[PDB]
Image (spheres, coloured by chain):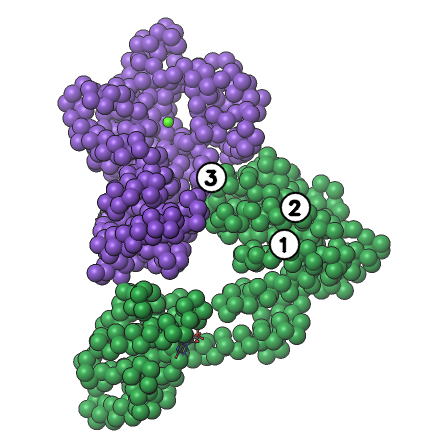
Chain colours: A purple, B green
Amino acid sequence: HHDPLTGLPNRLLFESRLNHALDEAREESRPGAVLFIDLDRFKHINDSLGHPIGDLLLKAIAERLRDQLRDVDTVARLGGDEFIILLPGLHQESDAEHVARKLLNAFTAPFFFVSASVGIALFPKDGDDAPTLVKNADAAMYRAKSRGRSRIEYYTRELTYLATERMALETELRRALERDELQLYYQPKLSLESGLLVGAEALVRWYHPLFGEISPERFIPLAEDCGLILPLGDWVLEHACQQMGEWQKLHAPFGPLSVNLAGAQLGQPQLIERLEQLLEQSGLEPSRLQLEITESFIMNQTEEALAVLHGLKRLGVQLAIDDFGTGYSSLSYLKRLPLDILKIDKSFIRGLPDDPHDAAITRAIIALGRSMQLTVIAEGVETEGQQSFLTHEGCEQIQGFVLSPPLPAELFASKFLKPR
Amino acid sequence: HHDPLTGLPNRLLFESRLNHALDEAREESRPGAVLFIDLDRFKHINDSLGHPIGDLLLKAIAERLRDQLRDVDTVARLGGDEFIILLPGLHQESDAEHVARKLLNAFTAPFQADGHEFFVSASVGIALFPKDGDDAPTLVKNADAAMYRAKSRGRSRIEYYTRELTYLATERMALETELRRALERDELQLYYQPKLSLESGLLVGAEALVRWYHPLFGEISPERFIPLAEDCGLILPLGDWVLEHACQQMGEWQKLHAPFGPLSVNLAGAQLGQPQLIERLEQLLEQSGLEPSRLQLEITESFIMNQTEEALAVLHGLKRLGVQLAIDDFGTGYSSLSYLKRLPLDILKIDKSFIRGLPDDPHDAAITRAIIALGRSMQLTVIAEGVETEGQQSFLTHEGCEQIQGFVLSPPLPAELFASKFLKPR
Ligand SMILES: Nc1nc2c(ncn2[C@@H]2O[C@H](COP(=O)(O)OP(=O)(O)OP(=O)(O)O)[C@@H](O)[C@H]2O)c(=O)[nH]1
Ligand SMILES: Nc1nc2c(ncn2[C@@H]2O[C@H](COP(=O)(O)OP(=O)(O)OP(=O)(O)O)[C@@H](O)[C@H]2O)c(=O)[nH]1
Ligand SMILES: [Ca+2]
Ligand SMILES: [Ca+2]
Ligand SMILES: [Ca+2]
Ligand SMILES: [Ca+2]
Ligand SMILES: [Ca+2]
């Protein structure tokens, strides 16, 4: 009746408790919460460290989850790396919030560091029976996966379908290449000192007849999830290289071409040798290619990236840290990284210049970047006012809608490139 | 001859069965084991659920351990929340390890008391015979020490005996009593370290640092006795003592000498958890006739970046009083630039690790140069800590570091000596 490994109640027992909780709810109009907790990227840990460590980490997390709740509450392992939590007898519906953060914050400390995404389903608001509530909380949890990770999300009518949609995309992504469904769009970069074009970024567009245009931000995670990141990443790299190689012949220089590089790709053994090859074929000087690695990966409290990163520098490729400013980071480790560029996350820029918090952190990032001799570029710049603000504050480069949204090669060349 | 409540054999009966086993062990030349099991944080269980439940829990625990062992094996209640176990016949010492874990995993599942089920844990010490002793008392003693070791190296764990374990266990107990006494007899002492400004060259304040000398043990370092306090629940009493005395002295100094900057005091993580902190702090200031502006509370980064929603609201409350807030040991590990701004900080203290390498080390320079730029941008009074050499102070000045603190200025001084060395008349 209890999970042997963790000693926690099983799915069955839980649903018995939830029923009593539901009776309690309708008898004494006292709302409740069902939280679904799934661990962030646990396979990589099982492979990286082996079951021995895994089975242990689960026991540890189990305990720490219990130590965060009251005796009235219930914590169960639902199977796999998934814990379902029952908060009955909430005085107010908003209480589930404070208890959610506690649970999420239990993971901030170490155990070996792991993370988890939480989905909240309130009752009876979001369901009046066990299967429905469990099903919804899960759907919420998936939305936390959808929106980055290591976060909590609430259930909303729509996001049950959004969850099953993402699942569908994973299988279709396998056919993406066979069908001519992948494209590269290009976005210009602007330096504020001068008024000149200083480079561009390649973005991956995936089209599907059922689901329409899929966004790059949502595309890569999917490719990672279904283990196609390598094959797809290679396709993206090569086509980026090809495009730059072509432009070098039919158009005047505008700087380097930028591309997102997934951690999984950084983990490959033949990457550096692969890139050499690709750069040679297109007749490209290595520095003409810029690889963007997202901060959250680099700052996973495990400096496994250094080794490879230096190789890429010895190759001559430019390295940029992407989506910087959010979450946790290490200043010590930030300097040890051979980076040329630091990209300011959109979130902080979208608020410029009105919001003082965003403005405050933008300055901090700007000043931090110059101290560590890194070129600072702001991404998501949407208004002339933001550009002006960033210009005074001494941001070096901008990228976003003020200049141009992503464009197809032809339109991009047509609009921004000159002859030579 | 049996524990009434649990139905388990008491220590007298256990002793005879241990003695008999020892006899067989000598002749037959066979190894054995005595295991000491002490429930983990069971006081909290009684506090939150009450004896009636705790008794049922003990009864439940006792019965589950019984099931985990052979017939030749015997489980006994030594007394309180402590159980003791004997493994008479072992093929080899390796076998004891195996049996120890069995008993651990028995605490994995929760235990059933009335309607509910609660999880309890335990620490386990192991003593082998005749390796670790050939008589009952020393085997129990040594097995107990290992339990205390398991108790100190963490919990819900197992530990084997080692020659040095007994002393460590007693010392830890002694230091507790001595701390408890010192705290209760005002036998701790505050030392004071000056802070200088590089922008001017005049005093900018001072830090109050807790010291503890004991003739029998000598100077007990804070690194040693603060965890002790945290472990045996004396940190709240300690922090309160530190605050009051830190205030008193400053107040007294407000009258006697002239204003020389504010006084900084470290605020342990748990002190922030105190619900009455703000109420209590205000009184402390009022009593000493100290403007809140005169007092600064230093809080370690590692803790503040681990903070919750309850912590940020308090930090505001502390500012509402007018006291200054400072982030201590800054830049070492992983932190959040986003969360750093939302804090109403006034001061930023650069960790001693980055400043002790100045200026020869290239990395430590880059980071120190970064932290200054960071603090400046956020409008935070940046201050170097642990400044030892002149070359280090030089560097910090050419790199725009506002304030400074360390041996280069002066080591922590006793009150009289401080007042006589850095303090001028009202
Ligand atoms: N060590 C251990 N691993 C388990 C256990 N149960 C499930 N897992 C692992 O948990 C992983 C589940 O991964 P998913 O939830 O599919 O995806 P993920 O790798 O966690 O990454 P996300 O998609 O971010 O959740 C699998 O690799 C399982 O082998 C267990 O009892 N012990
Ligand atoms: N209900 C009940 N409680 C008992 C009995 N005997 C001892 N206890 C409790 O067991 C607790 C023993 O606490 P300690 O061993 O001093 O420390 P702890 O709180 O267990 O924490 P540790 O440092 O991990 O041992 C006390 O709070 C006692 O009240 C008993 O017969 N019945
Ligand atoms: Ca998972
Ligand atoms: Ca899962
Ligand atoms: Ca990017
Ligand atoms: Ca105990
Ligand atoms: Ca300090």
Q: Amino acid at mark 1?
A: Ile
Whether callout 1 and callout 3 share a subunit is answered no
Some atom of ligand 5 lies within 8 Å of the CB belonging to the residue at label 3:
no
Position in image of residue A17 (x %, y %): 28, 55
Q: Amino acid at mark 2?
A: Arg
First-in-chain label (2 vs 1): 1
**In 3D space, how far apart are the residues under numbered discs 3 and 2 (Cα atoms)?**
37 Å
Asked if A228 appears above or below B32 in the picture, the reply is: above
Disc 2 residue crowd, few under 14, some 14–19, many 20+, Cα 10 Å = few
Q: Secondary structure at mark 1?
A: helix
Position in image of residue A156 (x %, y %): 33, 34
Identified at 59% across, 48% down, the residue is: B315
- The residue at which mark 2 appears reads as B320
Q: Amino acid at mark 3?
A: Lys
In the rendered image, the quadrant that contains the N terminus of chain B is bottom left
Asked if B146 appears above or below A173 in the picture, the reply is: below
Q: Are marks 3 and 2 in contact (CB under 8 Å)?
A: no
Of badges 1 and 3, nearer the viewer stands 1
Q: Secondary structure at mark 2?
A: helix
- The residue at which mark 1 appears reads as B278
- The residue at which mark 3 appears reads as A335
Return the residue nearer the eye: B223 or B367.
Answer: B223
Return the residue nearer the eye: B267 or B216.
Answer: B267
Q: Are marks 2 and 1 in contact (CB under 8 Å)?
A: yes
Identified at 38% across, 48% down, the residue is: A29
